[PDB]
Amino acid sequence: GVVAAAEKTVLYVGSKTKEGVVHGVATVAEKTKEQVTNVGGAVVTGVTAVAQKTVEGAGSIAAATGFVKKDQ
Amino acid sequence: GVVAAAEKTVLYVGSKTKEGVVHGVATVAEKTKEQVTNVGGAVVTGVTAVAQKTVEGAGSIAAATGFVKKDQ
Amino acid sequence: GVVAAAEKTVLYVGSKTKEGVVHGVATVAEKTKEQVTNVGGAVVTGVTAVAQKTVEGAGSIAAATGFVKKDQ
Amino acid sequence: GVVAAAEKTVLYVGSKTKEGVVHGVATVAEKTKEQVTNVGGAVVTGVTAVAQKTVEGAGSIAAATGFVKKDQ
Amino acid sequence: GVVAAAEKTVLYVGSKTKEGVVHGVATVAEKTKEQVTNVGGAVVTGVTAVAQKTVEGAGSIAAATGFVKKDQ
Amino acid sequence: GVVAAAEKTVLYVGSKTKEGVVHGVATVAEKTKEQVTNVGGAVVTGVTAVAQKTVEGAGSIAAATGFVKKDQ
């Protein structure tokens, strides 16, 4: 004889604001042979799961902003 | 004889704001042979799970901002 | 005979704000042979699980900001 | 003046046999509320990325093999 | 004047056999509230990244093999 | 004047057999509230990154093998 029993019985102006956010990312990269041969320049690779937030400014997440030149 | 029993019985201006955030990232990178041969330049690689937040400024997460030149 | 029994019975201006944050990151990098041969330049690699927050300033997480030159 | 240069110049009976194998699986399960209320039975749930290989035997990966009864 | 330069110049019966193997698995499970209320039975949950290999035997990875009964 | 330079110039019966193996597993489980209320039974949960290999035997990785009964 086996017997079992269970018996159970306000302005919020910017309030909850989730932004510039990255969450829940599962990334497998098995074999990526990255051979980056750069001469005289700018290179950006492999930016994953990145966040930024600015106020009163100029923001670039991954910018290949190559050259400035000025002669006078 | 086996017997078992269980018996159970306000302005919030910026209040809860999650931003410039990265959470919950599972990343396997098995074999990435990174051979970065740079000559005379800027290179950025491999930026993962990164966060920034600025106020009154200019912010770049991963920027390949190569060169400035000025002659007078 | 086996018997068992269990018997159970306010302005908040910036209040709780989580930002420029990184949490909960599980990262396996098995074999990444990083051979970084740099000559005359700037290189950045391998920035993982990084955070920054500025106020009244200019902030770059991983910036390859290569060169400045000025002649007069 | 900026100058840069780069200069580059036997039976095998069971030999390499990959079997009963699982590789390269990226799985996000955000919110699965698993409420498994079992009474008097067998239940199996949530078998992911599993492998088995037998020789001279009887193998079940995830088998809900409920009951045997014998009276004499 | 900036100058840079780089200058570069046998039976194998069971030989290499990868089996009953699991590799390279990135798994995020954010919120799975597992409430397993079992009474008088067998339950199995949450088997991830598991391996087995047998020889001359009977093998079950995750088997809900409920009951045996014999009366005489 | 900036100058830089770089100058570079047999039976194998069971030989290399990787089996019953688990490698390279990145697993984030943020919030899994596991409430396992068992009465009179067998329960198994949460088996991750597990390996076994037998020879001349009967092996179960995670088996909910509930009950045996024999009366005479």
Image: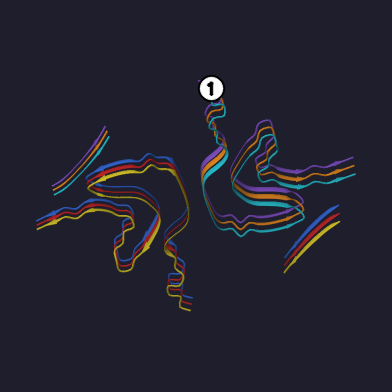
Chain colours: A purple, B orange, C cyan, D blue, E red, F yellow
Q: Residue at x 70, y 52 (%)?
A: C43
Q: Nearer the viewer, residue C25 or F18?
A: C25
Q: Residue at x 48, y 79 (%)?
A: F10
Q: Kindly indicate the quadrant of the structure image that contains residue E53.
A: bottom left
Q: Residue furthest top?
A: A10
Which amino acid, by three-letter code, is at mark 1? Leu
Is residue E30 rendered to the left or right of residue C5? right
Question: Up-down: is C56 above or below C65?
Answer: above
Regarding mark 1 in the picture, which secondary structure is present there?
Answer: loop
Question: Up-down: is A9 above or below A5?
Answer: above
Question: Up-down: is F60 above or below B12?
Answer: below
Q: Nearer the viewer, residue E18 or A16?
A: A16
List the residue tagged with mark 1: B11
Q: Nearer the viewer, residue D61 or A42?
A: A42
Q: Residue at x 52, y 30 (%)?
A: B16
Q: Nearer the viewer, residue B4 or F26?
A: B4
Is residue F16 rendered to the left or right of residue C38? left
Q: Position of residue A64 (x, y in %)?
A: 70, 44
In the rendered image, which quarter contains the C terminus of chain D?
bottom left
Q: Position of residue C26 (x, y in %)?
A: 51, 49
Is residue A72 rendered to the left or right of residue D25? right
Q: Position of residue D71 (x, y in %)?
A: 11, 54
Q: Chain of mark 1?
A: B
Local crowd at mark 1 within 10 Å, few (<14), some, or many (≥20)? some
Q: Position of residue A47 (x, y in %)?
A: 61, 46
